[PDB]
């Protein structure tokens, strides 16, 4: 069923985003005398977040590819894919167990137990589909007489788990540098030396993108609602017998959320407008989408420091913006492959909304590059001015594009 | 556009769920000598979570009703509804500001500022639609000549904000018992003394349900990933130079997540199977759905205590299960209204999957009622046995239903 995939992508997007939580609240204030240690901690949190997001995205891609061939789904497959969701959910904790405890073989053992678990869940799904082949994709067996496709399906869904099991066996009593056998789970699908590897549909990848955009836009208000509300005892504290004082004190956090939700929401708007006119995505499009989502998940942190010299924090925020928006612009740049089967005819080269899409997606990279140029001038606190300009232009952007095209 | 509503419902579901975060981690351990204060704190967190979920659901219903009449959407309306998302997002914090600081008029002022903000955003959306009436619903003005419908739209979208403004003005220098003028925002839509009030579509309400189910299933693994991983210094701590000891110590949390995700996932499965065969929902269906989602959002807490005499905690968990599942069973009970326009013909009274749906939705209420009966016996620790039985039966539930129907 198509609709179970909606819950699938929502839950897997939340799982992909789980790692940004320790990243957002990371004691950014340098009042403690452990600045080098704090920077090392930020480095490891960003690294683990990126790696976990990539791993969960790979798992989600595998799940949706499996559910393309078995699109028709009964209740039993619903329970089986719920078990698959259990396993994908437990993957990030095992990855974190690796990262925090590298030398201990137990982390490798648990992560590969998780990989074997997801693999055997997929294998059970495929076996149940095979035993009653009425719910497959319409052309796999309802139209094709080749049942040998089952062997390829089993291979693609079990190559990873077997390699992870072998890597765990190696790590038990061999050199722990055998991390590459685990990298094989992404290496082998990446290479195509030997219809399973068809690119992901626009609907599912866009649903994942929408879910991750929603969670990264809302996580900062999650932080606000956690403990940023003034306490009943706090009004007696600080000798401020009023609520205006506490609200003003917590105000910069609210300005941070203002900027964060604004930037993330308009990035989602640009991503959406890009994905309105795509009809058949490519693997490069999926890779650029996952990279862009990984780098846009970090905007909460970037704005969280830039709200609190500070030119370096503004630089970090603008660099995150630049990365997260160039990885969106690479999607639209990936039209030289073929405009016929990737983009709608109305948005083709020399199209009706042609320059509209160019500019509507290139303003954010343009804004970040102008910030990079502005770093030279001392009054480089234009990111707030950039915030206002970049949120005000799309309201009148149609008029600006019409004026540019008139000449 | 239909698809922008997907991001709408995802973000608004996350906003509706934001309040369960302080509820989940609420120092349940009674080792502190403030047990009465702890119980009072739990009471206020549950109350604020329920009220906030109801308020955000009302806001989401208003938003989706507005976007039914203006379903065709351009970029400008995308930015406007993003601003509406800003306002709906900020609503829960203002509600919490009320709850923590009741007597202070500032909380009322800020919440009504938020209400006026969402109201004026809706008003701007309606005005932009009116000035260029090419993107309305196909029958509002593309087929109906009555432009007076604009007055009713403005009334329905501005009656709430005006009443909240009046209530704030009252609270400024009158008795603060004027909370009822704010209850009017839900009272007036509830009453129908005087096509805007058409019941919500199955797609949107089911998308909201799927989003909230995903977040409530995943929030416990969020808690696990936050700080439940053993620390690099923790292995030196407790004189346990190994990882097995720390993993076993944090094990009951993982069993809690096992049970939580299992119960929430199968409740989502029951809800989904219920919503496969509905084609036109009613207002009673929407009310029962929002009530059920509110009461299923609390399962994380319930299992969080029941993992950690304890018969009372098991009782709380089973009571939450009972409420969250009777409020689903009331959906299916609401078929006596009309099976023709609510349920698919294959699932009508005396249908093919008739007893299938009855039992498939009634097992969880049956399990909770059996737990209530089992509380009498001393060995009432059958909820784990109930967990295993209730997750094992749906795998073979089709066979059980076939055997029952054979006789």
Image (cartoon, coloured by chain):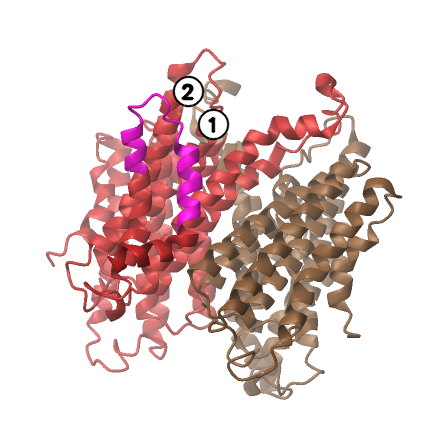
Chain colours: A red, B brown
Q: Quadrant of residue B206?
A: bottom right
Image position, residue A88 (x, y; %): 40, 50
In the picture shown, does residue A63 fall above or below A232?
below
Image position, residue A368 (x, y; %): 31, 37
Q: Main secondary structure of the magenta part?
A: helix
Q: Residue furthest left?
A: A193
The residue indicated by pointer 2 is A38
How crowded pointer 2 is (Cα within 10 Å; few <14, some 14-19, many 20+) is rated as some
Please indicate, yes or no, whether residue B298 appears anywhere in the rendered image.
no
Q: Give the number of the disc on residue A26.
A: 1
> Is label 1 in a helix, a strand or a loop?
loop
Q: Is residue B268 left or right of residue B134?
A: right
Q: Residue furthest right?
A: B175
Q: CA distance from mark 1 to mark 2?
A: 8 Å
Tell me where the magenta segment starts and ends, as one range. A368-393
Q: Give the number of the disc on residue B292.
A: none
Name the residue located 35 percent from the left edge and 64 percent from the top edge.
A276
Question: Image quadrant for the N terminus of chain B?
Answer: bottom left
Q: Is residue B116 left or right of residue A361?
A: right
How many numbered marks appear? 2
Most foreground residue, B175 or B100 = B175
Name the residue located 32 percent from the left edge and 53 percent from the top edge.
A360
Question: Image quadrant for the C terminus of chain B?
Answer: bottom right
Q: Is residue B51 left or right of residue A345?
A: right
State which tag comes first along the sequence, 1 or 2: 1
In the picture shown, does residue B177 fall above or below A272?
above
In the picture shown, does residue A13 fall above or below B72?
above
Image position, residue A131 (x, y; %): 34, 74
């Amino acid at each position: 069923s198509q609709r179970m995939l909606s819950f699938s992508d929502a839950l897997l997007s939340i799982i992909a985003t789980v790692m940004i939580l320790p990243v957002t609240h990371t004691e950014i204030s340098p009042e403690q005398q452990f600045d080098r240690s704090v920077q090392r901690l930020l480095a490891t949190r960003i690294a683990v977040y990126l790696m976990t997001f990539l791993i969960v995205t790979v798992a989600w891609a595998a799940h949706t590819r499996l559910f393309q061939v078995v699109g028709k789904t009964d209740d039993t497959l619903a329970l089986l894919n719920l078990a698959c969701m259990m396993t994908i959910t437990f993957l990030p904790y095992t990855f974190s167990l690796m990262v925090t405890f590298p030398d201990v073989p137990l982390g490798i053992f648990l992560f590969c137990v998780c990989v074997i678990a997801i693999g055997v869940v997929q294998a059970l799904i495929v076996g149940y589909a095979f035993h009653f082949p009425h719910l497959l994709s319409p052309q796999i067996q309802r139209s094709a007489h080749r049942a040998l496709y089952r062997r390829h399906v089993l291979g693609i869904v079990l190559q990873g788990p077997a390699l992870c099991f072998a890597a765990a066996i190696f790590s038990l009593f061999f050199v722990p540098l055998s991390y590459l056998l685990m990298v094989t789970v992404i290496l082998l699908p990446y290479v195509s030396k030997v219809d399973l590897h068809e690119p992901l549909s626009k609907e599912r990848v866009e649903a994942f993108s929408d879910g991750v955009y929603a969670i990264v836009a809302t996580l900062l208000i999650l932080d606000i609602c956690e403990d940023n509300v003034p306490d009943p005892k706090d009004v007696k504290e600080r000798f401020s017998g009023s609520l205006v004082a506490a609200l003003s004190a917590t105000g910069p956090r609210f300005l941070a959320y203002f900027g964060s939700f604004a930037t993330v929401g308009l990035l989602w708007f640009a991503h959406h407008s890009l994905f309105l006119h795509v009809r058949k995505a490519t693997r490069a499009m999926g890779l650029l989408n996952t990279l862009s989502l990984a780098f846009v998940g970090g905007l909460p942190l970037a704005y969280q420091q830039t709200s609190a010299d500070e030119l370096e924090r503004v630089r970090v925020s603008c660099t995150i913006i630049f990365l997260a928006s160039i990885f969106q612009l690479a999607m639209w740049t990936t039209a030289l492959l073929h405009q016929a089967e990737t983009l709608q005819p109305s948005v083709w080269f020399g199209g009706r909304e042609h320059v509209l899409m160019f500019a509507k997606l290139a303003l954010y990279p343009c804004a970040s590059l102008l910030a990079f140029a502005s770093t030279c001038l001392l009054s480089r606190f234009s990111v707030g001015i950039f915030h206002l300009m970049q949120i005000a232009v799309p309201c009148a952007f149609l008029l600006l594009r019409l004026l540019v095209g008139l000449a």
